[PDB]
Image (tube, coloured by chain):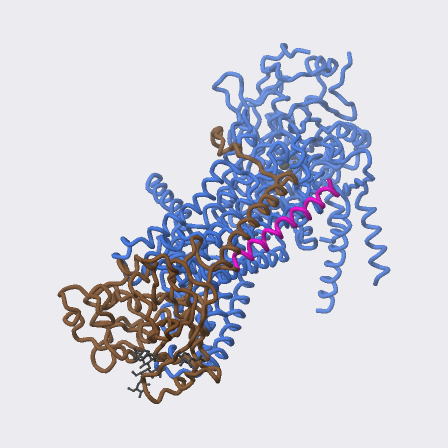
Chain colours: A brown, B blue
Amino acid sequence: KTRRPDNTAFKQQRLPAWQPILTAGTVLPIFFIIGLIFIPIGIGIFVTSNNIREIEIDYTGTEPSSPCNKCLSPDVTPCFCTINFTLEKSFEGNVFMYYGLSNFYQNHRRYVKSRDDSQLNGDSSALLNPSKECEPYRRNEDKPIAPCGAIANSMFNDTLELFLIGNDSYPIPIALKKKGIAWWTDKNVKFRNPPGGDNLEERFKGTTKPVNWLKPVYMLDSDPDNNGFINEDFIVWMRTAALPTFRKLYRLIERKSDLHPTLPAGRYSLNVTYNYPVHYFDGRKRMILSTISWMGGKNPFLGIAYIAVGSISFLLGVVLLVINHKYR
Amino acid sequence: TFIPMNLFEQFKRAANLYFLALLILQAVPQISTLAWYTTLVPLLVVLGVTAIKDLVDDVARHKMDKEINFKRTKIDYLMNYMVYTIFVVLILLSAGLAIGHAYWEAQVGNSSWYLYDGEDDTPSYRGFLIFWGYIIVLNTMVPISLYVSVEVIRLGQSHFINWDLQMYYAEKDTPAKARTTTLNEQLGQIHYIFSDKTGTLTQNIMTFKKCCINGQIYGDHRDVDFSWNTYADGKLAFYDHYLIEQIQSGKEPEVRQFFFLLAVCHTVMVDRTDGQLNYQAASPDEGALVNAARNFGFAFLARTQNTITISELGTERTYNVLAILDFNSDRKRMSIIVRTPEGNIKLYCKGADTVIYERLHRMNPTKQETQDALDIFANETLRTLCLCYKEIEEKEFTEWNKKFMAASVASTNRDEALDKVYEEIEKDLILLGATAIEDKLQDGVPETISKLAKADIKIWVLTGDKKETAENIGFACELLTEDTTICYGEDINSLLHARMENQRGNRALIITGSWLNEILLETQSKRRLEAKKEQRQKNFVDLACECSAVICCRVTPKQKAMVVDLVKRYKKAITLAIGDGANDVNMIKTAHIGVGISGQEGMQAVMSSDYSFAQFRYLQRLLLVHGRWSYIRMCKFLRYFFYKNFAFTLVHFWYSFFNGYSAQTAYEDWFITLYNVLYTSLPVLLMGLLDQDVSDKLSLRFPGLYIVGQRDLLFNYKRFFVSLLHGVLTSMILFFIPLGAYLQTVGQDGEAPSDYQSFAVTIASALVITVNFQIGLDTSYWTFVNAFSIFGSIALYFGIMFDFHSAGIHVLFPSAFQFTGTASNALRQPYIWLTIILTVAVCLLPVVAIRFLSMTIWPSESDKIQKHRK
Ligand SMILES: *[C@@H]1O[C@H](CO)[C@@H](O[C@@H]2O[C@H](CO)[C@@H](O[C@@H]3O[C@H](CO)[C@@H](O)[C@H](O)[C@@H]3O)[C@H](O)[C@H]2NC(C)=O)[C@H](O)[C@H]1NC(C)=O
Ligand SMILES: Nc1ncnc2c1ncn2[C@@H]1O[C@H](COP(=O)(O)OP(=O)(O)CP(=O)(O)O)[C@@H](O)[C@H]1O
Ligand SMILES: *[C@@H]1O[C@H](CO)[C@@H](O)[C@H](O)[C@H]1NC(C)=O
Ligand SMILES: *[C@@H]1O[C@H](CO)[C@@H](O)[C@H](O)[C@H]1NC(C)=O
Ligand SMILES: [Mg+2]
């Protein structure tokens, strides 16, 4: 019929190969070695996370007796809460200020998609032609909404500030800087203003503000590098969270010039303009101050998980060892 | 052309049409939860790769035209059932979450002012709309590349049969061929083997040994070189002096007639140009018999339409040929009518004694001891062809000859009109004697018949040769040993009648074809007859399959395919038919796996088969190496293919709870595209082609490993839901370990991977590594390309993903590519890598522990010999 088949390693099923078999002397060391690797990492992360100092102030006022419950029914648009908290142990180094939102589904399909990417990327064509994707907020009355979409529309628009109550009882404001609170790529690549011109007023011609926003996107900040689509607060909002209960970076408190702690232990008051309504869907607002750590942030779950898995792997090795010993 | 290509790819295959129906679902925007990219690109590649496996054939056919001018596997049936099971599970889960979204929307969705879209859709409608949303996000449960991967697995495995060098016969220079590239796993599931005897269990390299005429047996040592005869050759080794001088001198009419018949009743074409009077016989019996006849001076020189050129001891006497009664498996005997120059019409005949003795003359004193002679030759595995002759009166021949010529009336009449002439003349026959010819078992057949029996393959042999020769050949090839209590049809017949009327180690069933029909007998009355037919037919198979061996004798081609059908219908056992010669093609088509020996009878019953190697000896490697590996390589492929796909989509089902059941994809939109084709497609294919539980030499030495496939222990309908339970858990771990790690702080600073984009990068990353590490656990043959594909899959993902999330690609598609700066930011943070390591360790270590316990507590035979390297 045909000639002799060629004699090559692949064709004759004779490729050189290692035949690993899960011998009792091979699975056991990896199980115990994992026990001696996860545990020290698990205790390492746990104690490192437990060292982090954090304070979470829930200032939504849903519960009665909180002395700004009036803001749940804001007859006057400007409402204010003054929540006092005292820190037992002073914060050291950079202190990060976040705002938290709970039971707030930022990962809804109708929500995450509702946005125009070319518009935020600084596309002139898409500036006056919002995509169909941000359908419910394409245009307000006659001309398109510049930050279209259900995401840019429902933006966290509270005004959080911190005061230090010293012995004199006079509130001393503590510096909060709004710059450098977004990913480098988001500021420098993903989000951009429309091209052309120098004044932001002339760039956004034929575009209104979103319906919920009180003021246009032109002057979200006085800094020319922080006004428009490249605004730090706005960018931090559009970065959709993965779960309902999230918290987003708001302000930074960098190291003080003096050797004293950045936030010395003492009486502080949180002066916040209650603008965001969340009590309709049982949403909770929180203000979170956290201190920087070299090994990420405060993640007690991983430390407990590594210890939990580290112990299971060590136990599994012993259990597997016993079974091998009996059935040897 | 190509337009027909996709036309039958879609309709014929349910999965291929399922995804086309999905594009329509993804086209409409009111329910499109995934982009159209997510289905075309995995579809075009699957529809593109399969085109290459068939288009290359057509273009070759087109070139051929210019130059010149069904069997479905058992798993193939299961695979269809799995895919129809995934549809139901997908429809139930999609309907289950559709309920959950309507109730979520009614309570939380309607009260949520941020999720306002301006479309007053009632919560019952919003749930309905997202029922199609979860037919799209969770669509990938149905494996798109299952139907293309299996073709590559089977094609590659089949091509190992062609390239095999141990399955290659040198002197005849014909390697093994696998002419069906879809029956590979079924070679490892064979329960029965039906084999021809002559040409399959014997070489059909024949030589004349003995003889008997008028009761006097010749060919023994009593009272040599044939130099006295010019036509003779030394190839024939004969030691019988008495017949040599008797035929040389003092010749008698008996020996003259007997040898003359062998050189007249033949049908062998002859050549004389070489000067040695070469012969080329289509039937080994005829060629050897004439080759033996010429050795004694009865040499056949030439033949034409009206005469012959036979020679007798140098006396070249030319006869006249009038009619030749053709031979077939039904007739079982050949005859020729020849007119001598004297003017007498002499009819010669030969064939099986069974059909010739019934037509003998009343006066035949040599009939009795000739039967004893015939039995004597069969005792040494010698095929016997009885002879006979008769004379036809001139007066009665005229009308018969005219009728014989009139029988050639064209049309289909010649099928039986000739036969009517055949039986109307063959009334009285004068016995002459019987021949004795030697056939020898192929090399390593007794090794194979013993080897395959160790794998619990019941070897049935279906042979048209005599009762005695088959029984002794069965003993010769170790098919029947000294422990066998043979029984015949009468023993079977009595048992069946006894039970039928009442209700109204090694054993054999050596039974003749005549007794095969007798037991089976081959408005209300018709129904009862059909009921009787099924009752006895079912009783026979249950009586036959209960014994290790079976010998079927005097069986025509109709009775070969019949028996194969009986086992198939009434036992549900996979069958293999191996044979040579046109008589076996009826059974090669009936059997699940059809094997064809090239043999000496003809190159005919191999093109009508599935595998066409040269010798029965090679059946050791087809089943115990290629068939056995092909089964485990296919099952290991399926046990992982469902896992890697059913553990991929289920994150969408778990993430549905923390997003309002809104059908939000936990993965990147462009990661769903490449996962099925790019990230987790190469390593599984390389497994199904290059995996070996034990070495080839060590799989022959332990045929018991074959049993894993006969009983179907490696991929049941039960092990489908253990790979799904594996898929559910892996998706549960892949989701809830990242979720637990992000509910709390995760590297939260100016560069914080806590958003959703870093949630898709973490789950997808730990998913790619987990499956590509769990395939590494599956492969038992870590060749230097299995490692490359496994690590290539993981390294490829981190290469493309960086490119996709790189700032440069953002220019090409600001909208379609919207993940920029996530991969280069979500994996430089240690907590993300501490979550991926934990998500992989806690997802793979339980598999290692589960696998190790199974080895230690319930070791399999494959593992038992793998532990002992020697
Ligand atoms: C801060 O954000 C909140 C919500 O994110 C803003 O409340 C929203 O205010 C808009 C009006 O600017 C409301 O839209 C419509 O207002 C008209 C009156 O012009 C009213 O008749 C409609 O019924 C409708 O409410 C919107 O409803 C309201 N949000 C909610 C949940 O009711 C708020 O104005 C923002 N404040 C600043 C200073 O940016
Ligand atoms: N040309 C031929 N002339 C006379 N008899 C023949 C013959 N070919 C076969 N026979 C005889 O017919 C009987 C059956 O022959 P058949 O044509 O059915 O195939 P077979 O049985 O020889 C193949 P196998 O041996 O593998 O079963 C045998 O007994 C044989 O002796
Ligand atoms: C919070 O601090 C303010 C200002 O010091 C004070 O007027 C108010 O009474 C304090 N409230 C409580 C509950 O201590
Ligand atoms: C809080 O901030 C507002 C706005 O700057 C200011 O008017 C007020 O005096 C501050 N202190 C309060 C409300 O106690
Ligand atoms: Mg045969």
Tell me residue B130's x, y (percent): 44, 74
Q: Position of residue A36 (x, y in %)?
A: 58, 45
Instruction: Judge by depth and name the residue closer to the eye, A253 or B526.
Output: A253
Q: Position of residue B662 (x, y in %)?
A: 44, 72
Ligand 2 quadrant in view: top right
Q: Residue at x 39, y 70 (%)?
A: A99
For residue B222, side relative to residue B556 (left or right): right
Magenta segment's dominant SS is helix
Q: Quadrant of residue B85?
A: bottom right
Residue B204 placement, left or right of B841: right
The C terminus of chain A, quarter of image: top right
Vertical comparison of A319 with B742: above or below: above
Query: Image quarter for residue B65?
Result: top left
Is residue B672 visible to the viewer in this orientation of the structure? no
Asked if the magenta segment contains residue A310, the reply would be yes
Judge by depth and name the residue closer to the eye, B274 or B601.
Answer: B601
x, y percent for residue B361: 76, 36
| Image quadrant where residue B8 sits | bottom left
Q: Is residue B121 left or right of residue A223?
A: right
Please check the rendered image and state whether residue B397 is part of the magenta-colored stretch, yes or no: no
In the image, which residues are magenta?
A301-328
The residue furthest bottom is A75
Whether residue B723 is visible to the viewer of this picture, yes or no, is yes
Residue B459, compared with residue B540, is above or below; it is: above
As drawn, B837 above or below B702? below
Q: Nearer the viewer, residue B293 or B850?
A: B850
Q: Residue furthest front?
A: A168
- Total numbered labels placed on residues in the image: 0
Q: What residue is at 62 percent from the left and 34 percent from the top?
A: B616
Q: Who is closer to the viewer here, A307 or B18? A: A307
